Amino acid sequence: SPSLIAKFEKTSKSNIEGTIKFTPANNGTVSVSVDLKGLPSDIGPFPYHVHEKPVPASKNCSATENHFNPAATPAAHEVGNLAGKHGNIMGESYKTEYDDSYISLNEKSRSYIGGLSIVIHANNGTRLNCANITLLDEGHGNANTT
Ligand SMILES: [Cu+]
């Protein structure tokens, strides 16, 4: 299944910028790479989750609606609750890599995260920035390059 990326951009609403990248891993897991800067540290730590609807053109993070949620152990967390399972983002800059065995890159899979969104929150729940989850590579198919 194809890899995905969420690209966060700085605006008057937020200085958070960088990427979260999702690549398929061998043992039924997805490799997640987070590379973010510009975080407002003193209002963190920062939960982040996959939400159920796209970020619209207005960049209103509230319009992504709720968590993609289709605890004392990782599987008991919401699927989209990346932060609950793997750690809140924290600091002014944050770079980390981990495997998640609950999200899916398979179009035909129920836990597919393509076409959804990620929201980064302040610790109090306020939504700070958000990005759509889109294809990481432009060229696909078994006779193509990229
Ligand atoms: Cu969220």
Image (cartoon, rainbow, N blue to C red):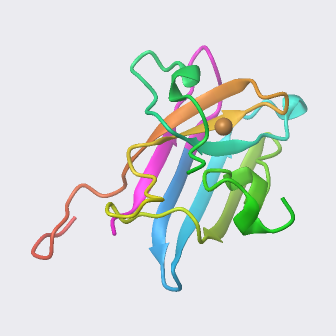
Q: Is residue 40 left or right of residue 119?
A: right
Instruction: Report ligand 1 position as a quadrant.
Output: top right
Residue 82 sits in quarter? bottom right
Q: Nearer the viewer, residue 85 or 143?
A: 85
Q: Is residue 80 left or right of residue 126?
A: left
Q: Which residue appears farthest toward the bottom when viewing the image?
A: 27
Query: Which residue is rendered at x = 60% and y = 34% of the image?
Result: 66
> Residue 46's x, y, as percent?
78, 40
Say if 38 sits above or below 71 in the image.
Answer: above
Say if 61 sits above or below 131 in the image.
Answer: above
Q: Nearer the viewer, residue 137 or 124?
A: 124
Q: Is residue 106 left or right of residue 99?
A: left
Q: Which residue appears farthest toward the front when viewing the image?
A: 70
Is residue 72 among the parts visible in the rendering? yes
Determine if the magenta segment contains residue 8.
yes
Say if 12 sits above or below 28 in the image.
Answer: above
> Residue 123's x, y, as percent?
84, 33
Q: Is residue 77 left or right of residue 66?
A: right
Q: Which residue appears farthest toward the right when viewing the image?
A: 42
**What is the magenta range?**
1-18
Q: Quadrant of the N terminus?
A: bottom left
Query: Which residue is rendered at x = 61% and y = 68% of the image?
Result: 100
Determine if the magenta segment contains residue 6.
yes
